[PDB]
Image (tube, coloured by chain):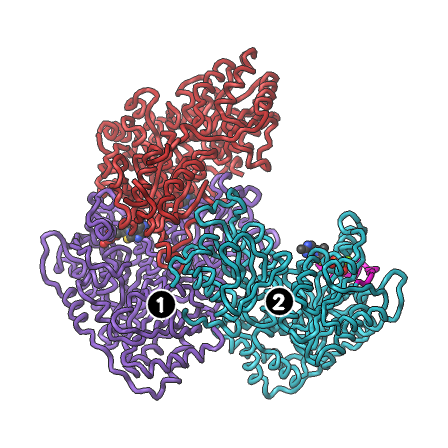
Chain colours: A red, B purple, C cyan
Amino acid sequence: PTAAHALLSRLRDHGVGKVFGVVGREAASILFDEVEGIDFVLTRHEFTAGVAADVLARITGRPQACWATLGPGMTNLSTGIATSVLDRSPVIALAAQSESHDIFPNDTHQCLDSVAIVAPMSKYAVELQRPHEITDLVDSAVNAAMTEPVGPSFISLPVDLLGSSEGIDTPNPPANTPAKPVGVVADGWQKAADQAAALLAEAKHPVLVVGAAAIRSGAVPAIRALAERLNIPVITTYIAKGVLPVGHELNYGAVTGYMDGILNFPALQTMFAPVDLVLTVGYDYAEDLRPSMWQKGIEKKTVRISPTVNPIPRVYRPDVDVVTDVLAFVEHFETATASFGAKQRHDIEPLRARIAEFLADPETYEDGMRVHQVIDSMNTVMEEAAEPGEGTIVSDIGFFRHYGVLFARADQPFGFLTSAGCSSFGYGIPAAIGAQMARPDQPTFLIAGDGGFHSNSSDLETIARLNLPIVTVVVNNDTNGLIELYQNIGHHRSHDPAVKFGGVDFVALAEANGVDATRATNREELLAALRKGAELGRPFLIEVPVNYDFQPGGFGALS
Amino acid sequence: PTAAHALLSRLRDHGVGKVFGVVGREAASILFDEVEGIDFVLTRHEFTAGVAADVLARITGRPQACWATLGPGMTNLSTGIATSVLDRSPVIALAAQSESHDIFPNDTHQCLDSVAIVAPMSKYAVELQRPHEITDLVDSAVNAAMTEPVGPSFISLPVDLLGSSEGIDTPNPPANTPAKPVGVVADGWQKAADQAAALLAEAKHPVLVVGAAAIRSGAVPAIRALAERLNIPVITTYIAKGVLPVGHELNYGAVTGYMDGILNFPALQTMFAPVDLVLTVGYDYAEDLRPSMWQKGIEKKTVRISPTVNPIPRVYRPDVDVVTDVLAFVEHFETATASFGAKQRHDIEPLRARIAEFLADPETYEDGMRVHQVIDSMNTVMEEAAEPGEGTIVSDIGFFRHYGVLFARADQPFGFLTSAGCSSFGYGIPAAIGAQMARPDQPTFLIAGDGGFHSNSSDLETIARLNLPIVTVVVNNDTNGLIELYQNIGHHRSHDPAVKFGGVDFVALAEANGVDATRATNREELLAALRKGAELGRPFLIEVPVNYDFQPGGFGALS
Amino acid sequence: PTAAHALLSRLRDHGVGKVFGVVGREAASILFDEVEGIDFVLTRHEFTAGVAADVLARITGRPQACWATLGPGMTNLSTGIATSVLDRSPVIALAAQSESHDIFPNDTHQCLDSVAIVAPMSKYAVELQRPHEITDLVDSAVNAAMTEPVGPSFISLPVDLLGSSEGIDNPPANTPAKPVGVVADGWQKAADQAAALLAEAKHPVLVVGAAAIRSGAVPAIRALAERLNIPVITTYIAKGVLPVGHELNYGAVTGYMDGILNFPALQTMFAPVDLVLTVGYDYAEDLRPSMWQKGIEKKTVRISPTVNPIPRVYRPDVDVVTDVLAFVEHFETATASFGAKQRHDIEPLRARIAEFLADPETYEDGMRVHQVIDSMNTVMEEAAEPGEGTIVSDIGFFRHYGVLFARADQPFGFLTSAGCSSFGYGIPAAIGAQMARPDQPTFLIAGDGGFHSNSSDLETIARLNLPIVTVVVNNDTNGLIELYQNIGHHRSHDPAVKFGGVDFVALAEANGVDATRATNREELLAALRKGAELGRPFLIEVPVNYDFQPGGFGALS
Ligand SMILES: Cc1ncc(C[n+]2csc(CCOP(=O)(O)OP(=O)(O)O)c2C)c(N)n1
Ligand SMILES: Cc1ncc(C[n+]2csc(CCOP(=O)(O)OP(=O)(O)O)c2C)c(N)n1
Ligand SMILES: Cc1ncc(C[n+]2csc(CCOP(=O)(O)OP(=O)(O)O)c2C)c(N)n1
Ligand SMILES: [Mg+2]
Ligand SMILES: [Mg+2]
Ligand SMILES: [Mg+2]
């Protein structure tokens, strides 16, 4: 009864039921059957393991776990670790190491200096040295992972020590897993919150800009109630879509810096130009809603609320900085603003008409579908398939992803999932896995482009193996499309060798992994394929040819 | 006329004609058309890019180059960088970074502290800060990469700075690209080489254990002629197979720690038991030919020759350490042993008969073929399709790979290619891309297992796009088979969730990528498929079902 | 029979006979009497320890050892370690650490992440984990320390493991006799391209750095300079590769020399030169290309047992990566048939230097440093056998006087820190020099700022009874820093550079070191001569001033 047993056992004490990963030669020291209640989920690549853990942690609000072997196992896991550190999830990342007496980084076969490599991208990074201490190392790893900003903690596991029973006796101290993240609180945050209240009283047209940290804090209903009483519009980051239901009058949409260019419309100015006060509730620069995007029209005052000290004062100098828990802020703020008269909210109907018209685009095109037609079709079938307040749409990374930000339906928090911080291509499959496992009885759709999807398409076999009924839509234009956009922004022409592919048959690709698939080229075909996939009870994949029709004109918000 | 131009231009100055990678939003600062004579080679994943550069650099003996975007681009590339640092190749690894004024690691969108992450796995790692200095940074990278132990040098490139002309005026100074690696040389190595010559004189059965460093030094012809004259047997690491031709009487084969167990034979004993002196020529612990593998039978004396100070005295205390250039050691050694009488070489025919017995195995099995029969067939068609002294068989990582070490034909240096130091699965495809480009007119076969091959299978599309006529054999037992072996060694049983896959049709998978394919299930079908493949003028893939029937007991030498 | 025994024992196997340091609570695990032939040398501060080890290692060409306790011990040592890495010496730096099971950097009492802190300023840094491995850690440390650029290797020692016998039940040491270096393929060819440039050149020179001394290349370089009539210019510590008076000894360079001499000295030394061969080049020594780039563009040849670390600054026309001696030997063969050269004229500069050193004036306030060093040279020529003696200089403005004017009659006859240049360097460098040359005279000159930064080790000099003679030149100021205020801002600001008075005579005497005051040439010469024959340490304080000219130091940019 070994450090391997103690490791899995202590993960179980913190609520972990799954370890995602790829096991290497450390299998001699750990089978993964040591502890009842914890199953191994084998992936085809370690990146998929890390991201699935990241996403499962986001939705459940609980620490999750991933696994890799030494050397290149750990470097492959590192892109999932990076997904967790930038996107913010409590992930315990574990990787094997050469035998302790044989650790010579870059000399011993497969031996890298794992801790030096991972420390800069993690909350906590350590190497096991005495087997019995693994219990305290898991606890210190959970501790750091669950402190804002939440993130991954890394433990490197030399193979001999992982298989040793030395110092281990068969009375586990309580876990005390935080039920929500530990945050930082400044003295006199209440006073700063009052100052923010005084700005709100003076303001004629305020907004709440909500980030995901507001969801982790459990502040969604409270923010909604605040917004409704005072008639304050709510604008979101990519993943805070769904903090208000679809069709709510205060749901002013999500922001992407690509929105003016995509909609051929002055969207950011319509959203922000008349605004005189911006409250960034649960702000986090990594979500990529930057100050420059709301600095439109008149001068604005700002209020930052975050359970962290502001790491970017070069970029964001709020008039009022409130360092405290988000829910605690909203409760204090409700009391301070109880006497305030409801505001007159600014008009964004022209932007709403523009969005609705992109989604309703009834044209049939020569080359492919347009991505807005694809998402609108995905919305229709999601709403049919899902109970109200349920369903997840997931987006991989690419130009199409920003169409997801503007157009995809989100009827609950995390109802639209993508990687805002790290934005690694191929994120889609592992995210759809994590999401479907978190929400077992809910439809899970994935949209991905050909570039990013194929970067990580091999874990289609994992989707089949686990029998997760994810419906995937690959939008194909045989290009790294986002990158062709940037070629054009910077140089006013393309260069195909850096961005162009030959053909891939994603239908045939899906079928080789044992996933049923079909091609769809217009709304009618796409709708039928989605509805078949949703009702299939097995995963399903739909390939859709697309084109973008871009005009490098309106993309200045990207500077 | 920008730092992008100055970067690509200085790579062209050091001989580089290709840059492998994936390009992100830095495409706004760099098209990859700025410089005649350097082309971009787009992959589906950055790992592929870094490994192709590593192999192309190994075979050409000249610095090569790979490329990634910021954040996850850089971390994906790092498995390639780790390949380069552990296998020893001179790679210039390049990654974009957030705009210089906006570099806040783990806060700014996609911003990771790239230098801190890569420095522990590289020879040199730096961030560009003033545009015109990109010329001297490239040189300093080449400098550190071409010093032994050769390895990767990393440059992080903030997007603003890459695209800036500030400080750049177009007359470039001379490159002085080292023609072969700069190495370290101890004072008095001539004296230590004479002590080694005196030990050779007084020895009944010496051997030369030859590592890849000896090939890098250009020492192969010289080693051959010393071995021939004095009747000294030559034993090699995985990748130094072919330093003598196949059939040569002194070609005593390659060592792998897995050999007694695969062969069910005391192969290490037969190979080393009566040997009284081991000359490890170009020794490098990373190749995984460890002292404990030749420590069989009688007390041996050892002589280490390397162009590096000994990094692992805990594990290898040679009787004579000769720190110098390998070629210079051999020339001095010829001089001091010119009048010595030739030796009686020891008999290893029992081992040879056992290896030949595996290769000739004519049994049809109920389940699939056996990997030794798979490799025998590849040897036959490689000898047919390749000129003498030519051809490359490439191996991915897994249990099958060590069958490769024992059985695969290699008629020149690097005629058998696999990753000996880092051993990342998915290696095969990119190593074969690199091998095929370095040897445009030679046949290039790849063998990979299903675990490893599917880990990086998406880059079949790259093989089709570049039209490289690589013949790929996938050996499929629906298992991470090597890992199931380690489960059985450690625990005396399997655990399927950590190692077992569902069905993947690699024939259909390849064809979905634009590569023609076919299933072969016995020697007759395999030979027919391999013959077709080698004559197609197009890539081809062959799926072969296999099984291992392993014997967990005979792998003691792995500890 | 403990890891402590095994560590000391392996240090003895590598020639080490002294460990310099300060011992903390790790004394419970290590006494320093476990091995005959290795003694402990207690200092007052760990910096002194590290620097004494660095200087003993440079002069002896052999690895040396220093020691500190955990946390602040190790950080104190680190200025010593920084001295070794920048100045180039093979030092084994040893520090204790918290018990292995209690290592929580920045939470455990006195616990710092020692390896992370020292890795960036060392050749090798590691923490002990299993007691018996200390033997191989010591060997890997010596290996990395004795590879060019030579430098310090650090081993962190948790107290429990240090005092444990677990697994402890010896193989040969193989200490390199001289540094391991790198060597490019085609270096013989690049050295021939250099000989072709020496043939086509009218006024070549040899700029020599200390790495030529480590290579054992000094005799060989003399011969090549004599036969081909090439002048030899040096870095601060390569002074004395040619004897005093030798016609080819063109002295040492320092970017402060134009400004101090009030004379276009670099112009004189380098204007008409057309080929510069930087023999054993090392940018850390602070003789930079800008200092020889006077007049006509020169061609340059670099010769170092290392690849060029600084191509942004020094792009030689020819780069010869190889051992220095081996380069010289191969260059002799290629230049065997060459006729001697016409060496350009620098008498005007020699005359200005001599004129400084002879300065007979008597200044109201106190002496001038050029007069102090002249008096030092005179008494050192008397006291010391020929080819012998050591003048050590601490850091500050006066040190650049030391570079120009101080007598060096052997390699390392003038000692200062060229690379790291920490003030307080002087005492420990004089301690190490005196120990390496037990029967030679050892003089130290230091300023009041630097001397006082590390003056407490006067008691160590007394305790070890090393007959060093120290001259503290006191102007109640960090004078060098006042100069830089004036270069940058055209005025002074006293709160950043001025002290009140310190009586260094009384300070010395408080430490049990005899001392006296001296205010002119005659008082100074009597003090030095008394001190050189005292058979005990001795200190002399001399009031000085500088009256410097800010506008003449354009060369420092
Ligand atoms: C790991 C990684 N490398 C490079 C990039 C740059 N990049 C971002 S999304 C993307 C994919 C774009 O192509 P695709 O998935 O087809 O979407 P499209 O833009 O064509 O709609 C790429 C290459 C990235 N995001 N992640
Ligand atoms: C990047 C990476 N992760 C994990 C491993 C552990 N591992 C080594 S090879 C391998 C693949 C083994 O399966 P397969 O390629 O089919 O070869 P087989 O052993 O079945 O013959 C695995 C999972 C690895 N080598 N590299
Ligand atoms: C550790 C350290 N801190 C600060 C300095 C800057 N500095 C260099 S030498 C020196 C001393 C200058 O005064 P002093 O030793 O009296 O010599 P002076 O310039 O007066 O001749 C100082 C402060 C330094 N060299 N080293
Ligand atoms: Mg695309
Ligand atoms: Mg397999
Ligand atoms: Mg002073």
Q: Is residue A462 left or right of residue B71?
A: left
Q: Is residue B44 visible?
A: no
Whole-percent x, y for residue C523 in the image: 85, 69
Residue C545 belongs to the span the image colors magenta: yes
Query: Disc 1: which chain?
Result: B
Residue C133 lies in what quarter of the image? bottom left
**Which amino acid lies under the numbered mark 2 shown in the image of this protein?**
Val
Q: Residue at x 51, y 24 (%)?
A: A271
Q: Is the CB–ligand 3 distance for label 2 below 8 Å?
A: no
Q: Is residue B276 left or right of residue B84?
A: left
Magenta-colored span: C541-557
Count neighbours of disc 2 (C-alpha within 10 A) and say few if under 14, some if 14 to 19, many if 20 or more.
many
Q: Which residue is mark 1?
A: B212
| B108 or A168: nearer the viewer | A168
Q: Which residue is mark 2?
A: C55
The nearer-to-camera label among 2 and 1 is: 2
Q: Is the CB–ligand 2 distance for label 1 below 8 Å?
A: no
Q: Is residue C550 left or right of residue B196?
A: right
Whole-percent x, y for residue B100 in the image: 56, 45
Quadrant of the rendering where the C terminus of chain B is positioned: bottom left
Residue C477 lies in what quarter of the image? bottom right
Residue A186 belongs to the span the image colors magenta: no
Residue A73 bears which disc, if any?
Answer: none
Mark 2 on the same chain as mark 1: no
SS class of the residue under badge 1?
loop
